[PDB]
Structure formats: C-alpha cells, structure tokens
Amino acid sequence: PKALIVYGSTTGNTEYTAETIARELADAGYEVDSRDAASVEAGGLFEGFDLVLLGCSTWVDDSIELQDDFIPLFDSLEETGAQGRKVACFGCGDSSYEYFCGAVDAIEEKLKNLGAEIVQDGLRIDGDPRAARDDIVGWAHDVRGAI
Ligand SMILES: Cc1cc2nc3c(=O)[nH]c(=O)nc-3n(C[C@H](O)[C@H](O)[C@H](O)COP(=O)(O)O)c2cc1C
C-alpha cells in the first residue's frame, strides 16, 4: 500500500512526529511519501494513495489556529481527492492552552465534511514528541490495522 504523510511544523515537533510514523509504516511494508505542507500543491494531491496522514501544530489565534504552512492546503482540501479516502490526523500542541491540539479537530471535521473516511481518532501530542515515541509508534500500528 502507498501512504502520503503531509505535515506543517514550525519548531520541528510535528515534523519529527511525521518522520516517526513514516518509519513505522515503512518497516511494516508500505511505500511512504512524506512531504512538508510548504511544498505541496492541493490539486489532486491525494490521487493514487491508499492512506493519507495529515498533521499540524496549533497556534493560538483569533481567526485560524493552524500552523501557517498548512493553511493553504487546509483552505483547498476540497480539491485534494479526499472523498472516500482513508485518512488519519496527528499534531503536537500543549495542554496549557485551551484549544489543546485544536488543529487536529479542525482538520478531522473538514475531512469528514468532504466525505473522507477517518480510520482512527487523531494522535494529539502534549509537549516533546521525542518523549511520546511509544504513543506515536503504537498509533501508527493501530492505523495500519484499520486499513
Ligand atoms: C505562541 C504559541 C502559541 C501556541 N498555541 C497553542 C495552542 O493554541 N494549542 C496547543 O495545543 N498548543 C499551542 N502551542 C504549543 C505548540 O503547538 C507546540 O509547541 C508544538 O509542539 C509545536 O509544534 P511544531 O514544532 O511541529 O510547529 C503554542 C506554542 C506557542 C509558542
């Protein structure tokens, strides 16, 4: 199976998380393409992929709390080929904030409105993901199991 991982990361946490999930899928036999949201184009981005994993960090804001590189993709999610696509989301944040990993909720709800199939509840990491390595790996393992 071919998996697409797209992440938006400012300080590297969600990017480390994306790389960790990418290895777990690769060791399990998937063909994985991992991309920074700052370099992709929304149009047909999901075409040909069996599984798509989207991730991003949350930044307190009055209009949109998604990490900046991910906003253009998020605003054009309806052109990516999300209907009937198997997808799962993940993101890093901090539980000291009211909207803890609120970007994950935002992305899940819009993929659900576009007809995607959410295969697992989202991975929400509090603090340094290097300390949650077990949780990332375990989540990646359960996502493969739902495909
Ligand atoms: C100024 C600022 C605002 C933040 N706002 C939130 C927030 O609204 N919700 C949340 O869960 N985390 C928030 N965080 C925590 C960051 O999302 C967290 O540091 C995350 O690991 C950053 O991930 P990244 O390196 O992949 O961009 C905020 C951090 C900073 C510095």
Image: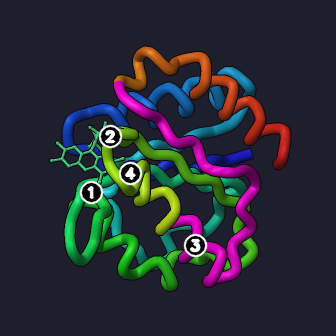
From which residue to which does the magenta span run?
A: 107-127
Q: Position of residue 84 (x, y in %)?
A: 75, 74
| Residue pointed to by mark 3 | 109
Residue 123 inside the magenta-drawn segment: yes
* Ligand 1 under 8 Å from disc 4 Cβ: yes
User: Which residue does the image show at 21% across and 66% down from the upper left?
Assistant: 61
Between disc 4 and disc 3, the foreground one is 3
Q: Any atom of ligand 1 within 8 Å of the CB at mark 1?
A: yes
Q: Is mark 2 within 8 Å of ligand 1?
A: yes
> Dot 4 surroundings within 10 Å: few (below 14), some, or many (20 or more)?
many
Q: Nearer the viewer, mark 4 or mark 2?
A: 2
Residue at image location 43% in from the left, 50% down from the top: 101
Asked if residue 117 shows in the view, the reply is: yes
Q: Marks 4/1: CA distance?
A: 6 Å
Q: Position of residue 127 (x, y in %)?
A: 36, 28
Quarter of image, res 10 = top left
Left or right: residue 131 compared with residue 13: right
Q: Which residue is mark 2?
A: 96
Whole-number angstrom distance, CA of label 2 to CA of label 3 = 23 Å
**Which one is in front, 128 or 15?**
128
Type of amino acid under label 4: Cys
Nearest to N terminus: mark 4 or mark 2: 4
1 vs 2, front mark: 2
Question: Residue 112 is drawn in which quadrant?
Answer: bottom right
Q: Are marks 4 and 1 in contact (CB under 8 Å)?
A: yes
| Image height of 24 relative to 62, above or below | above
Q: How many marks?
A: 4
Identify the amino acid type marked 3. Answer: Glu
Label at residue 56: 4
Real-space CA distance between mark 1 and mark 2, rounded to the nearest whole angstrom: 18 Å
Residue where numbered disc 1 is placed: 67
